[PDB]
Length: 172
Image (cartoon, rainbow, N blue to C red; front, side, top):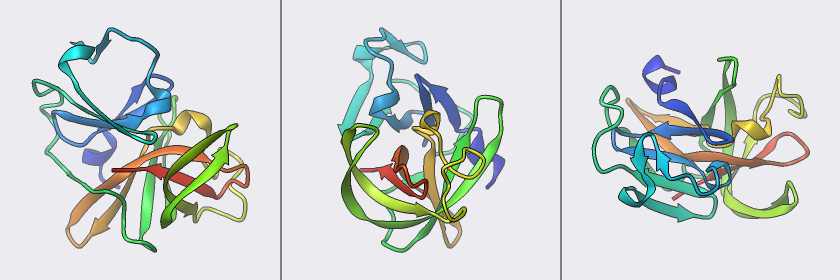
């Protein structure tokens, strides 16, 4: 994917999040650190926080990433869409993982109940290795697809099955 996209993926608590716009940031609820006072300098109470499932969406009172143009964010992709999960790792590896997007669904995973738009990685037979598939620290990395000339953000990675291939894109 373009570099204008990858620079939007910064660290956030125990994973990642993504600057949709200068003002608008998405991540996984399970990566948000417990009772911080502040996010990106701004105090918690001045941020508009929206949560649906494990999907989290911060809108800041002033612009923070003046460098990025605003993207399209949608409530998931059409069923069957091949999307990319844009994984960053701590040592700066960029790992675009192709995923066929399924329907909204609920699973028990990593000892808990999750929902969102389900997907399968198109990365191998059994993407259990972090060479081929996700790792717990990838939570909050974004799912994007190209619709003609626009890039569309559909949400963030929040969980993966033990099988390696099945994954949840938290949405809305």
